[PDB]
Amino acid sequence: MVLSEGEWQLVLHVWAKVEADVAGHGQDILIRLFKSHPETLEKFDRFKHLKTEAEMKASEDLKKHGVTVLTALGAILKKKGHHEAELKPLAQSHATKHKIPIKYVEFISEAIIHVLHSRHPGNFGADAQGAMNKALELFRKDIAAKYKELGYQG
Ligand code: HEM
């Protein structure tokens, strides 16, 4: 797939607002994932033990991991589709070391969309949401293709 420049501008305009508070957004997204799809917490040996939303909110390690996730994602989005080099080591660790199925990448995509809609309603109307969904679909398709090349396709 290919996004148009106008689609990329919608994506990078709301992302610019996200970057005003990377740690806050990172925490909101991971907590939303774990609340909506509890099975995903089981892939994180580091976080597995946390029982409640309050415990998640108070975890400094979970907040640090949120910053890592969004910084990596932001670097990929800023490439506007030219992300083959950035994607390779991410696909390799998530297929081979962490063993993350593509369905769970769909689940975090949903979580990102929910948080942006909640925090940025004026910059995340229907057309901006459609553009962000397309950007995340492009990411998912490319990571799936790399999974298959690597021997997982899970
Ligand atoms: C937007 C999609 C994602 C991005 C950008 C992302 C990015 C990252 C990065 C940069 C790391 C650290 C370096 C590495 O190990 O590759 C990491 C670690 C990890 N990711 Fe992801 N990730 C994504 C989705 C997921 C999903 C959906 C899951 C599981 C449901 C997941 C599970 C893990 C685990 C288990 C680790 C290791 C955590 C630890 O340090 O104990 N990732 N991820």
Image (cartoon, rainbow, N blue to C red):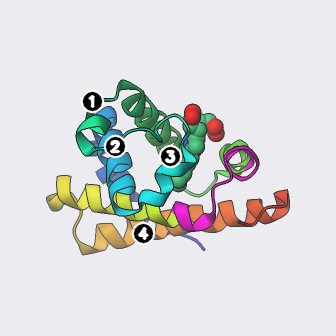
Secondary structure under badge 4?
helix
Q: Amino acid at mark 4?
A: Asn
Q: Residue 103 or 147: which is nearer the viewer?
A: 103
Residue at left offset 75%, top offset 66%: 153
The tag on residue 73 is 3
Q: Which residue is mark 4?
A: 133
Q: Nearer the viewer, mark 3 or mark 1?
A: 1
Residue at left offset 48%, top offset 64%: 135
Q: Nearer the viewer, mark 3 or mark 2?
A: 2
Q: Is mark 3 within 8 Å of ligand 1?
A: yes
The image quadrant where one finds the C terminus is: bottom right
Compare marks 4 and 2 and give the one earlier in the sequence. 2
* Mark 3 burial class by Cα count in 10 Å: few <14, some 14-19, many 20+: some
Secondary structure under badge 2?
loop
- Residue 138 vertical placement versus 93 (above, below): below
| Left or right placement of residue 6 versus residue 126 in this view | right
Secondary structure under badge 1?
helix
Q: Amino acid at mark 2?
A: Lys
Residue 141: image location, x then y, percent: 63, 68
Residue at left offset 47%, top offset 70%: 134
